[PDB]
Image (cartoon, rainbow, N blue to C red; front, top):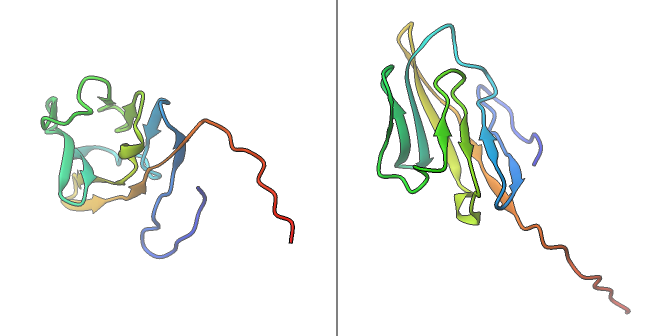
Length: 121
């Protein structure tokens, strides 16, 4: 996965191997001081919310193995699964009084190698 977008908010495309510890970190590090920090698994799906108090997991399977760092705001997933591959959206409420949302298309790959297929016209 490499760069491939432009505008006032390029899309993030990360790629890792299945069953490996990943780390979701928004390009731009959290501002001076954020107010709200939540993670979205899908278009209308959440994973964990942080009300400037204590992380809150919304009955998300991830809960248990994953972990949300309120210091940086990164999501660490263990023994990830091919399914994990999805558009991640981290919504945060800026102190000033704004609302931003990033995007990360997680791309999981398989470890097992591949054979040597050759074609002879």
